[PDB]
Length: 81
Length: 67
Image (cartoon, rainbow over all chains, first blue to last red; front, side):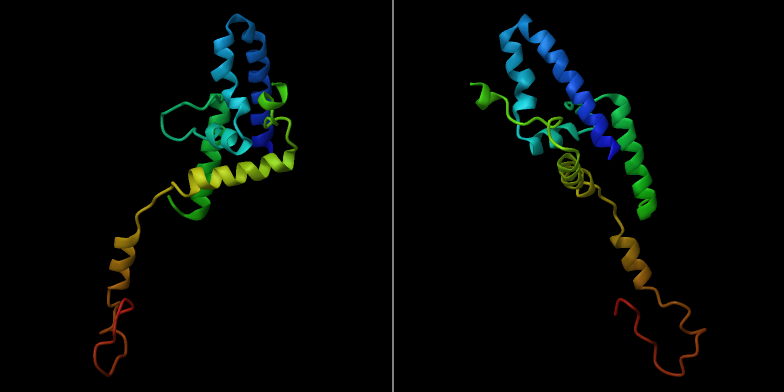
């Protein structure tokens, strides 16, 4: 519930930044809005890459930490310590 | 041009649709990729005759759970 709301707010803020910065270079806009032009399933799949150290996901570290803590709590509840 | 480029972003989508997409993505990205090794421990535990001679048997050695 709240994880996706925070993700959507962050995505809106990033999109606003990309609109503010698009006028600098048109070629920049192409791969900067590739994310927003991808299908929604791909968008959320590629935003859910906090695992490992690839760090290609454009997501805040605190937002990553919330999911990394929930995933540890879920493993503890599932008994996969 | 505009219609081709600007398809529905995530933030435009309603809350419940985004939640369902997050559930599917979280599943296939984290839950499936999560790996823990238990096969050797489980087989070793199942292959142990547990206190059978102390237990009342009055017969041949009872088959182990793996058996």
